[PDB]
Amino acid sequence: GPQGIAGQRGVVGLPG
Amino acid sequence: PPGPQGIAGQRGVVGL
Amino acid sequence: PGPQGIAGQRGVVGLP
């Protein structure tokens, strides 16, 4: 059988 | 069901 | 069942 739904979007990267 | 849900994403890369 | 979901996709980088 297939695998689970893809994980939640990760939080944005920082600037300087 | 397949899987429930994948693990949440971690942060993006920081500044330079 | 299925195994777990694919991991969450990381967020978007900053800048100089």
Image: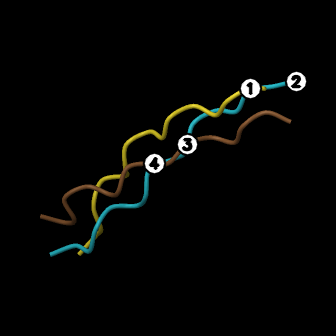
Chain colours: A yellow, B brown, C cyan
The secondary element bearing badge 1 is classed as: loop
Amino acid at dot 4: Gly
Mark-to-mark CA distance, 2 and 4 = 24 Å
Q: Residue at 45%, 48% (x, y): give it.
A: B9
Which residue is identified by label 3? B11
> Relative to residue C12, is residue A8 drawn left or right?
left
- Mark 1, chain letter? A
Place of residue C15 in the rendered image (x, y in percent of width and height, measured from the top left): 81, 25
> Relative to residue A2, is residue B12 drawn left or right?
right
Mark-to-mark CA distance, 4 and 3 = 7 Å
Give above or below for C16 relative to B14.
above
Mark-to-mark CA distance, 1 and 4 = 19 Å
- Mark 3, chain letter? B
Give a yes or no on whether discs 3 and 2 share a subunit: no
Which residue is identified by label 2? C16
Amino acid at dot 1: Pro
The secondary element bearing badge 4 is classed as: loop
Which residue is identified by label 1? A15
- Mark 4, chain letter? B
Rendered image quadrant of residue C12: top right
Give a yes or no on whether discs 2 and 4 share a subunit: no
Kindly indicate whether the residue at mark 2 contacts the one at mark 1 (C-beta within 8 angstroms): yes
- Closest to the observer: B11 or B7? B11
Amino acid at dot 2: Pro
Q: Quadrant of the N terminus of chain B?
A: bottom left
Give a yes or no on whether discs 1 and 2 share a subunit: no
Kindly indicate whether the residue at mark 3 contacts the one at mark 4 (C-beta within 8 angstroms): no
The secondary element bearing badge 2 is classed as: loop
Q: Residues within 10 Å of mark 1 (few under 14, many from 20)?
A: few
Q: Residue at 22%, 73% (x, y): give it.
A: C2
> Relative to residue B14, is residue B16 drawn left or right?
right
Which residue is identified by label 4? B9
